[PDB]
Amino acid sequence: GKGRWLERIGKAGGIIIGGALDHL
C-alpha cells in the first residue's frame, strides 16, 4: 500500500523545507 505517500509528512515545516524547494 503506497499510502503513506501522503502520510510521509505533508507539512513542509510551515512551508519552508517544501517552499524552499531543494533547499535552494
Image (cartoon, rainbow, N blue to C red):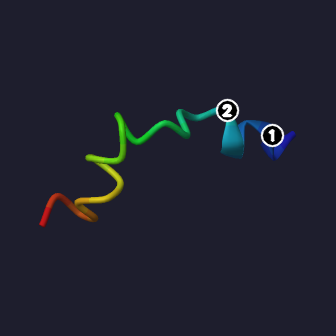
Q: Residue at x 35, y 54 (%)?
A: 18
Q: Which mark is residue 7?
A: 2
**Left or right: 23 as drawn, with respect to 12:** left
Callout 1: 10 Å neighbours few (<14), some, many (20+)? few
Q: Residue at x 16, y 58 (%)?
A: 23
**Left or right: 3 as drawn, with respect to 19:** right
Q: Which mark is residue 3?
A: 1
How many dots with numbers? 2
Task: Please report contact status of discs 2 and 1: CB closer than 8 Å, yes or no.
Answer: yes
On-image quarter of the N terminus: top right
On-image quarter of the C terminus: bottom left
Q: Position of residue 12 (x, y in %)?
A: 40, 42
- Residue reaching furthest right? 1
Q: CA distance from mark 2 to mark 1?
A: 7 Å
Q: Residue at x 80, y 40 (%)?
A: 3
Nearer the observer, disc 2 or disc 1?
Answer: 2
Q: Amino acid at mark 1?
A: Gly
Q: Position of residue 9 (x, y in %)?
A: 53, 33
**Left or right: 11 as drawn, with respect to 14:** right
Q: Residue at x 36, y 37 (%)?
A: 14
Q: Find numbered disc 2 in the image and state the secondary structure of the residue it sits on.
A: loop
Q: Find numbered disc 1 in the image and state the secondary structure of the residue it sits on.
A: helix
Q: Amino acid at mark 2?
A: Glu
